[PDB]
Structure formats: structure tokens, C-alpha cells
Image 1 (cartoon, rainbow, N blue to C red):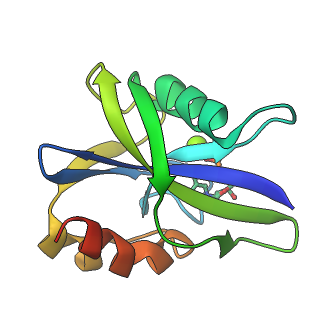
Image 2 (cartoon, rainbow, N blue to C red):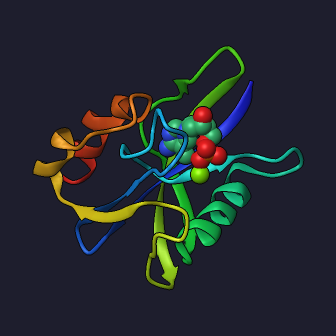
Length: 126
Ligand SMILES: Cc1c[n+]([C@H]2C[C@H](O)[C@@H](COP(=O)(O)O)O2)cnc1N
Ligand SMILES: [Mg+2]
């Protein structure tokens, strides 16, 4: 299974969430940003690559956040905690970004795959 890595960036007590712009089925819905791992890459290398590209930030990749999610037969989604080293997030590849607190998490229009992490994200912001 191809791995997709996603980042739960928590900064000053809030969580970054990113509103997708593609494809049509996901455009308008919110995610933990990330992307596919390239063969040869560690999860950490891939996720730091994706978040530099998409958000314009340098992050450190930490512990897992929640469990693996099955996208399809081919693909598995994995979330990690990440923390900021340098830079401020900007939506280079998204419709919008939003910093949310615990009480906002379950109200967001999540990408259905990511919605699985809602209890984990609420816990992390407890
Ligand atoms: C980063 C991410 C990605 N995906 C799904 C959407 C695509 O089917 C696939 C690859 O992601 P992308 O379109 O490269 O961001 O994984 C779902 N949740 C996420 N948090
Ligand atoms: Mg992406």
C-alpha cells in the first residue's frame, strides 16, 4: 500500500487545518495537510517536504496522531504530530487555512478519510 502522510500542526494551543481545493469531491473540505511518500523517503522526510511545499513552513515530525486510515486497497493515510521550526503557514496549495481549538474540531467539514481522527485531535487539544 502506498503511504500518504498528514500533519497535525499544533501551535500556541491551536491546530492547523487546511481546506482542500481539489479534486471536486474534496474541494471545500478540510484536512490535515500532507501527501504521498516517494519511494526511498522516510515518513518524516515526505511530510516535512509536503508541508514546506504546501504551507511554506519548516516542521519537525513527531509521534503518530491516531491510527492508519484506509483510503483504498492501494493507499494508507497516516497522521503525525508536527511542530513549527520556522515560517508561518500560507495556503499555497489550499483554498484556506484555519487555526482551530478543541471545541471546533468536530464541527468542521472534514474530508471523510480524515474525519476518523476527530477524537484523537480533540484529545490532543484537551
Ligand atoms: C493529505 C491527505 C490526502 N488525502 C488523500 C487525497 C488523495 O486521494 C490522496 C493524496 O493526497 P494529495 O491529493 O496528494 O494531497 O490522499 C486525504 N487526507 C489527507 N489529509
Ligand atoms: Mg497534499
